[PDB]
Amino acid sequence: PLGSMSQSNRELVVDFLSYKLSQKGYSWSQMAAVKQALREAGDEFELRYRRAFSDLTSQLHITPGTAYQSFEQVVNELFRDGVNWGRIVAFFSFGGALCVESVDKEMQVLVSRIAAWMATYLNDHLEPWIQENGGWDTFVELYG
Amino acid sequence: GPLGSMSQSNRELVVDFLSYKLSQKGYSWSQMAAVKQALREAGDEFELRYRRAFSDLTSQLHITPGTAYQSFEQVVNELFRDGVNWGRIVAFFSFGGALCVESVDKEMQVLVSRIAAWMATYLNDHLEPWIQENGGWDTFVELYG
Ligand SMILES: Cc1ccc(CN(C(=O)N[C@@H](CS(=O)(=O)CC2CCCCC2)C(=O)O)C(=O)c2ccc(-c3ccccc3)cc2)cc1
Ligand SMILES: Cc1ccc(CN(C(=O)N[C@@H](CS(=O)(=O)CC2CCCCC2)C(=O)O)C(=O)c2ccc(-c3ccccc3)cc2)cc1
């Protein structure tokens, strides 16, 4: 395709420059700032709640036969008493540990499926809360 | 609810976060994510190993709001004087990264998008034929770590 290398070269340039800027406390864009804040928040959460997070990840083990409903059931228990930014971070971290576990078990095919389940969950459940609570820009200000 | 603008940006956040978690354990979301990660790490390794020599390189270009592509190209051309290799491509990315950081430090934020476009032009004009001839970015990933 005519524009393939332009498009992938630009992607590589943007990624590398976003990374270099973030290392010095700068950001390529507002979306890059949201991504960075969420990456760091996930590390912080996983470190502070290591034992409690281990109890959560033990609740679900994805197989090629696992239905979205099983993921949605576990994630729903995480938000039964309500939503907050910390619980949203825990949701992202949970999805990340399910993907890690899938590749550990040589089921890399499940990674794209988990990503699609996470995006479905966010769309079906969490957008009204994100919007009412100032959006991802408020998360960046609260985290930083 | 319905599939609006927030669902698309939320999917982008999911992909970015999963890519980051997988990379922490030595895994990758995709081949493109693997290239991006290898280049990020190679840049860090280069900047650490050649800190003094790299400082001499970055000092060669005095960026200003009037700096043209030609001035970046002159300095970069010197870097590839003895030919192209993966290490000098890593040094080229690191150089562009340091110029962006310097621009923001000096409150000339406008130059960042100008540097990204210079890098893409230099990449397409001078380095891409060599990259295709030498196994592409996938070979760089296999060679690196
Ligand atoms: C990065 C980060 C994430 C989370 C916590 C912990 N935390 C928390 O501090 N809640 C605050 C209210 S808030 O969420 O708005 C605070 C912050 C969150 C980060 C962005 C800015 C706003 C509070 O109670 O005052 C929790 O809400 C929480 C605790 C445990 C779990 C859990 C642990 C294992 C398994 C299943 C759930 C989930 C969430 C700290 C730091
Ligand atoms: C991460 C990493 C990057 C680069 C070096 C250094 N290096 C190197 O080792 N080059 C070899 C081998 S290679 O490049 O084909 C492939 C290597 C390097 C890239 C990842 C895969 C493995 C060679 O001689 O060809 C160089 O080519 C080099 C040295 C100095 C400079 C410089 C330093 C300051 C200012 C201006 C120039 C630039 C490049 C080490 C580690």
Image (cartoon, coloured by chain):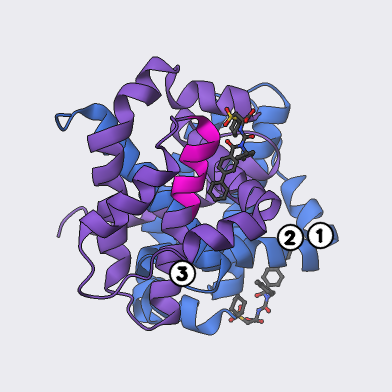
Chain colours: A purple, B blue
Which one is in front, A29 or A38? A38
Residue B45, how many percent across, how many down? 70, 67
Residue B28, how many percent across, how many down? 43, 69
Which one is in front, B37 or B56? B37
Give the residue at x 45% y 59%. Answer: A96
Left or right of residue A135, residue A49 in this image: right
Give the residue at x 21% y 53%. Answer: A3
> Which residue lies under the disc numbered 1?
B51
Q: Which residues are magenta?
A: A84-93
Res B66 visible: no
Residue A73, how many percent across, how many down? 30, 51
Is the CB of the residue bearing disc 3 within 8 angstroms of ligand 1?
no
* Residue type, mark 2 in image: Glu
The residue tagged with tag 3: helix, strand or loop?
helix
Query: Does B106 appear above or below A9?
Result: above
* Residue type, mark 1 in image: Arg
Find out whether the residues at labels 2 and 1 contact each other: C-beta distance under 8 Å. yes
Which one is in front, B117 or A47? A47
> Which residue lies under the disc numbered 2?
B47
> Which residue lies under the disc numbered 3?
A100
Between marks 3 and 1 in the image, the one whose residue lies nearer the viewer: 3
